[PDB]
Image (cartoon, rainbow over the protein chains, first blue to last red):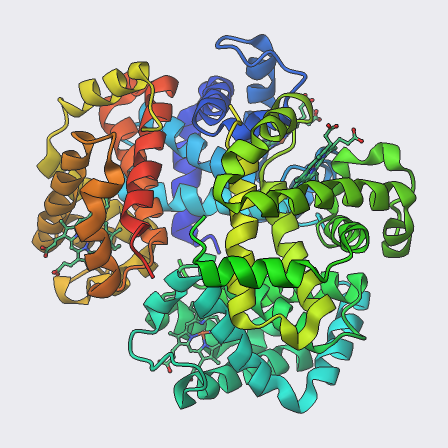
Length: 141
Length: 141
Length: 146
Length: 146
Ligand code: HEM
Ligand code: HEM
Ligand code: HEM
Ligand code: HEM
């Protein structure tokens, strides 16, 4: 459950991400592919090399969805409905992978928000990403 | 999310368990301790020898809690409220361990309900245990 | 994998009673029913619309046969699972793109199937031994991923 | 090991710049804040009520230093993590009763701390090398559990 302080932390941190959200989405994916190679099995059709525009493009979509989630933090299930449908019924990514991207998003944020990434903010972001993950995997079965 | 069909499936299987719920709860614990020895780290104060009163008593409490949840399958959060508080603030069992007991409960049910453990019931029970686990872990942070 | 001799024997003994084709079809079908996301690799198998359709699909049964036949052969090499599954590991990564998490799911479904099949004979110690084997195989198949 | 030469150089280089005292304290404090259930092992450490309390606790800072120092030793024996941590593995199991899942959580928090501390120098490839180490260490510490 996201407390009022959690929501405030997330909105502040994401606020600072601002226009960089896309770049950070791509970096997080890159971190994911290198750190947890099993995640690459879901993108056999991509050029996963450093700098790949496919990863950059996908990074932007992930980041935009997260922005949408932040904007609708009190109504996540509805805001992310089409995305829940897509992951559950078409992409069918094992739920385990959501924790790996989440960790990589956190590392990316840490690396770019020295000042903002306090222990309290770190905790709120982790809860937020777990919340997003739960929603995305809500309709798997 | 448990569908109506799921709830019917669970109530059916659990019904069959009936009066053996406590013995099944004890067996599931013994199966967990043997298969996943790291789970023993939460029971250093117990005699974990086969058939010990402590394990049998605990298995009974676990089974009673599960019965409670089946009974109030539509309102688990409220029915397991006290238990979710106990696990979150006192016991503080890492969430990973819930999946291990859930698997061992499933094996126990399988070994004892030859007629009732169909693919559909198996799916419903799995979802049910995941649901109980989620509720018990709900207040962790 | 860390199996004492006691354990290897408890594995071998029960396995001699298994109908590999039957258990294979059951385990694969149950994986597809219980964790529907795993269906992602099998759209060429036809109808997977319901539990009944899955359980009865001839392609599912044939695939289960193939998978469990390889598993079965691996039981003869408990001591060298990694060497035994190396080429299969590579194929699953490089050509089939199967997330190794699927191997763990199957392993757990297999244990549920044996328990259902064997009832009381599937004791806590026997389960413990099979848990080690199933973890071992999963690890062996994920070993060559990169 | 699990690590490659490029990866060992990566690991070794960054580690030369870490103030073990400082990073240790940060890593343990963040573990206690982000995954509060981990506080079950430190009832005697005092005030752990709020992030500021956790982070400023001298006992947390002290313990963090102890842990990372032992962690540093392992960096010196990347080729024999199991041999290196055998004694501590047994201690954590037999006397402390620590669920090894806690080793995994700490590894992830440590990565977060390094990224926070080093910024842009903590590149994707460097992270990947550290993920291998942290997993290796956690496996080494869980090795003697029974
Ligand atoms: C925070 C968690 C995640 C979010 C917000 C997210 C969001 C999205 C979005 C917005 C899209 C594009 C949908 C479209 O094309 O309309 C997408 C597609 C996709 N996602 Fe997810 N995703 C998440 C996690 C994951 C994970 C963990 C994986 C696997 C490791 C994954 C694999 C994919 C794949 C394979 C596609 C299709 C890519 C393509 O063919 O272009 N996603 N996701
Ligand atoms: C389906 C999941 C679970 C249910 C329904 C459940 C239920 C319960 C219940 C009813 C109690 C007794 C409370 C009392 O005495 O008032 C309890 C206590 C306890 N549980 Fe949970 N539990 C679950 C999972 C777990 C897991 C996975 C572990 C650890 C691996 C665990 C560890 C404990 C411990 C250590 C106690 C205290 C026992 C004692 O000191 O007597 N539980 N649980
Ligand atoms: C114990 C675990 C497993 C073993 C031993 C195993 C073994 C095999 C074998 C022997 C083959 C045939 C290889 C060949 O064409 O020469 C195969 C193919 C395949 N496996 Fe696996 N498998 C396992 C688990 C899985 C899982 C869990 C999945 C997906 C959920 C999967 C997906 C596939 C697919 C899609 C093929 C290709 C089928 C075809 O071309 O007809 N396998 N596997
Ligand atoms: C990087 C992994 C870790 C390493 C290398 C490590 C190492 C150590 C060392 C060197 C000691 C002191 C031993 C002595 O008294 O002679 C210790 C004690 C201890 N560790 Fe670990 N540790 C690690 C992770 C953890 C984690 C994650 C936890 C729990 C969250 C934990 C809980 C404890 C506790 C409770 C003690 C006893 C402190 C006391 O005596 O009050 N450790 N550890």
